[PDB]
Image (tube, rainbow over all chains, first blue to last red; front, side, top):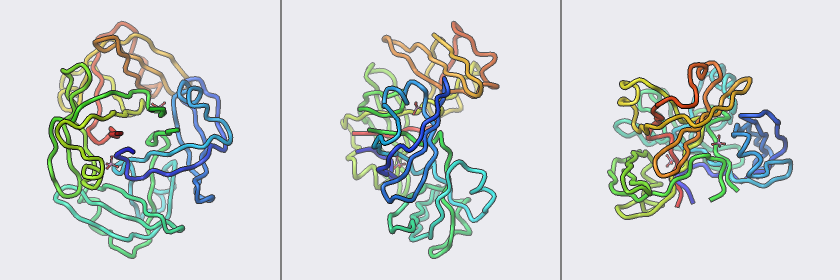
Length: 137
Length: 138
Ligand code: MOO
Ligand code: MOO
């Protein structure tokens, strides 16, 4: 139980063996969503992040951007196309809920000034870097 | 308790605001002295019961930690922890920087290799990070 609003079960499919910071590939339990995640070398060993390892991905809401710009999405390490299902606008931040293709709901916290063109029903892309995710067992 | 976050600290919530979408909490760490500021969604603040007295674990991933020697940068950040670098591991793209904290703790930061060339073991530095870079776990 953590504050991260996006907690996705998945499985390690690959892991590199760089000495300071390593990357792993994760397939989500929906069986289609692939993610790239970076972790320190000590952590990859300590957690035993080898092919087939089941894990829980923790992606805090503010680490997720929501964009209508395909280049922004393509520049990021991870891209999850979807459809905005709900928008709650606060004074300083916005909660953007996005329906993923499988029906799950992604949550992003976006600065109010970056959500002015966003509206429910729009096709957008959720994006984040590999080093913005925590792996939990 | 088993997560990749290299920094995992016990703390007690000592304050919480009730802003609509994103709220902030003050967290007093295990040393009974260090206070952090953390941002969470309103839904999470209620779901987790992040009220005064609530004990939690702070998860801070290595790449979220900046290292500086500049007073302004440290003061401008939401959280800053002074320490001394105890070890550096240089890599082709990233460097692991470990910093000794009071009461035998070690903070771990992952810094891009081209930004850590002036960092060296034994320097007095300040680690810093945003309120919205921390995850709170029950
Ligand atoms: O820790 Mo949150 O509620 O994903 O911002
Ligand atoms: O090893 Mo990490 O980068 O603290 O998740």
